[PDB]
Image (cartoon, rainbow, N blue to C red):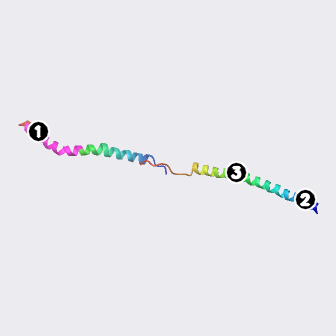
Amino acid sequence: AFELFTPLFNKIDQTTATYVTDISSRAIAAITPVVSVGLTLGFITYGW
Amino acid sequence: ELQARIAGEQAAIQNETTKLQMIAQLRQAEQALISEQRRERNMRILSSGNQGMPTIQ
């Protein structure tokens, strides 16, 4: 059968996932705990 | 006897003439068959029953 747009769309989706979505997820997940604790401690310190 | 021998010789040349005609017909038939094979190959390449195409991967 004729299958051209399904493979192409899947390929592009894989490229966007590996290189635009995963990298953003990796960066946010790495900074979420540290930024969370830092923001909380900054709140306390600035209030005092 | 020599006259009948020469008559037989003429008959032999007649036979060669017929053989040459037959060879010419066979030559024409062979050319037609080669053309038919060419067109069979052409039809096989361009047949609308083909279902394949390159895949994106």
Are both tags, 2 and 3, on one chain? yes
Mark nearer the viewer, 1 or 3: 3
Q: Is residue A32 magenta?
A: yes
Residue at the spot of label 3: B31
* Residue at 37 percent of width and 44 percent of height: A12
Find disc 1 in the rendering and name its residue. Answer: A42
Q: CA distance from mark 1 to mark 3?
A: 95 Å
Labels 2 and 3: the sequence-earlier one: 2
Q: Which residue occupies 55% across, 51% down?
A: B50
* CB within 8 Å, label 1 to label 3: no
Q: Which residue is mark 2?
A: B6
Q: Under tag 3, what secondary structure?
A: helix
Q: At label 3, which amino acid type do we have?
A: Gln
Residue lying farthest bottom? B1
The type of residue carrying mark 2 is Ile
Q: Which residues are magenta?
A: A27-45
> Decide: marks 2, 3 in contact (CB < 8 A)?
no
